[PDB]
Image (cartoon, rainbow, N blue to C red; front, side, top):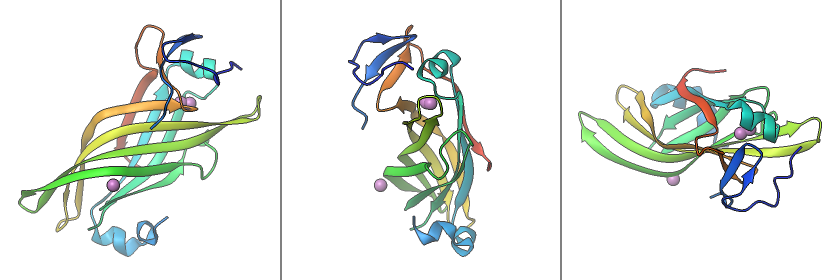
Length: 185
Ligand SMILES: [Hg+2]
Ligand SMILES: [Hg+2]
Ligand SMILES: [Hg+2]
């Protein structure tokens, strides 16, 4: 297990470089009447890390959050399920800030800064680590028809692992792939 607790910006550690070191329950979400009456979407955030990162820090390659987002006059977020690699019930999905406007025909266009978190327990070291994903999302909602369109991720996703932002040694992302498609776990 590498010691990742005393790092500085710019350092190389194994196959990685350190880019940064200072990381930045409503009843409504569980009421099928609210879900019926409001624009909502159920999505999976599927994260696949590169092998060299995953093996080095001893964190599994594939992490998934099953989430819901709901628009309710505003943007409400909830983790429904996580992949079995994350500590049970440790997943969180939070909206930090939101901007929106009416664009006519009863549509609203929005951008939000959101973050996912979860804990991972290493059974060899018996230590728990924190995974964080920051992203800026864009969407559109139509309250009358209850339509919620996810129009993509504009900033991020940016992964922090135990409060450190890594890149590969060659400056590329530690992420192999990600998706934020409709679905549930
Ligand atoms: Hg990880
Ligand atoms: Hg907010
Ligand atoms: Hg990670």
